Image (cartoon, rainbow, N blue to C red):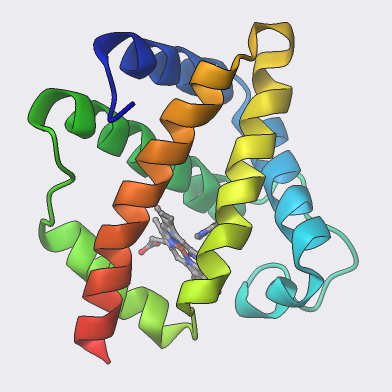
Length: 153
Ligand code: HEM
Ligand SMILES: c1ccc2cnccc2c1
């Protein structure tokens, strides 16, 4: 795909529907992360120590909202420029993920939760095109992050 204007339109659309209920969708997103990889709980500063995932926690909501925002912006960048660019922000993001003990093998985990989160957010308007645009947007932005990471350690 490498994002055609229509895949990019489709990603932009599901992102607003994402963004129309942050508390819900972001709580659902974390539930999904833990179901895939239980042990991932521990790397989150606002998850460990708890039973279940808080529903009205401000840091959780801002951090998961921002994750999704980054992937949607990569998707527009891929369409428009043809590449994902490495700017300050993403290099900062590399150092911070090395800090928190993130590895390359973790990235799949957060991809599948994002895929599944979007499937439930769009409900009947889910297509394979949507699934492939988001796959692509995620995989290109994680290649860039994976790079800054190995440059911070
Ligand atoms: C392209 C995929 C990813 C994106 C866009 C992303 C983005 C972010 C952002 C925006 C933050 C917080 C920004 C800030 O407040 O400075 C962050 C922190 C964090 N990320 Fe990610 N990340 C990605 C992959 C992952 C993966 C694979 C994991 C592993 C579970 C992960 C775990 C973490 C942790 C543990 C923190 C902070 C820890 C804490 O709150 O205790 N990230 N990431
Ligand atoms: C909150 C903060 C950081 C994250 C990074 N990757 C996946 C999920 C996240 C949620």
